[PDB]
Length: 261
Ligand code: NA
Image 1 (cartoon, protein in one colour):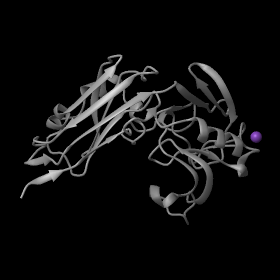
Image 2: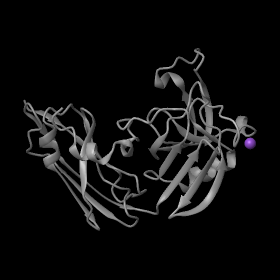
Image 3: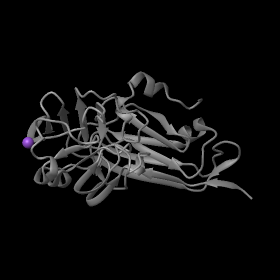
């Protein structure tokens, strides 16, 4: 009996995504030969751009260029793992493909010195939103965050992130208009309870609190792969292997890869 593993490729076939979206290939088993996996994945872009592979964990590899994508780029991915030994006799269960395109450049910068989140679309300021980020004891990390999933309404529960709800930094919070920007649990979301503090004082556990209307706007206009950059906070840097932290790894290190470690 064969040992098989199924690949899953993102983003979605035909999706339009932002300039920060990486190609993601996740397998349902640990990959013992990361080099075989990389060799089996073919990527074509138009206009052509150099890119490289980097593993976030034993099951998931990412591919991106050095710089954010050029708007209008079309990308084809073929994960040709059928017939490929991905290490220790674990074979690809199937081949998978995605074709996607890059939309407008959307980069929203949150500067702790001004407490404003400024959304720029192809270089042009379209919104200036007062924000309240993580208070000093639970700060928002600096760095480049890739926009992920969005929810009209959800609960953020700190136990998802290893912090008990009953503990001083714990929370179990209903939020409207929530756009996820890290797997570590940073979201841009509606925070009617911090509208006074927004633009002046950090009060959150690390999320970018903005007004109800600004969060709904963000929910409506920003898409997976668009960019939030956080600067000047008292936090550290979002980890490169967060899940949405890919761009915080310097290109030389990204390009060198981690196929053999
Ligand atoms: Na305010």
